[PDB]
Length: 100
Ligand SMILES: COc1nc2ccccc2nc1CCC(=O)O
Ligand SMILES: [Zn+2]
Ligand SMILES: [Zn+2]
Ligand SMILES: [Zn+2]
Image 1 (cartoon, rainbow, N blue to C red):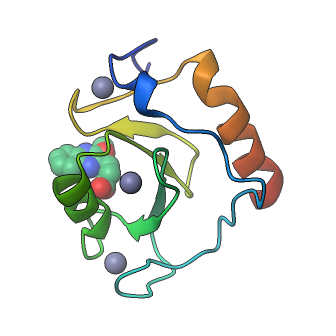
Image 2: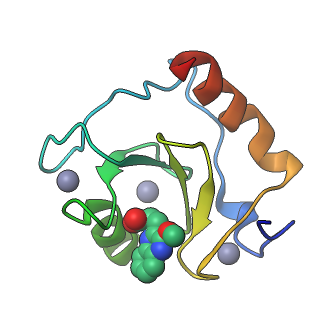
């Protein structure tokens, strides 16, 4: 199971009123594959198995927590773990409505 809390949930920012687009491509390479959205600034970048742009974004922003547009899991780069908590329910559900 994921961690039930982490000390970076404080950095999760309010969801844009535009909502989320789970088909949004990577902001850097344009791939449609394995994208994640950053839960601090809501930019979308690809996962480590494509071109690793979300990991790069973490490195040059320090933003902690990212949501997968594949399965709606949330990863913390600092804790190196999946996290789930009530603070993540609204953004997961917006993503779920857009995806399914
Ligand atoms: C299981 O998810 C990850 N494990 C990682 C391990 C080491 C380094 C980065 C990692 N990033 C993710 C998920 C987000 C991503 O793919 O960028
Ligand atoms: Zn990319
Ligand atoms: Zn960010
Ligand atoms: Zn964390």
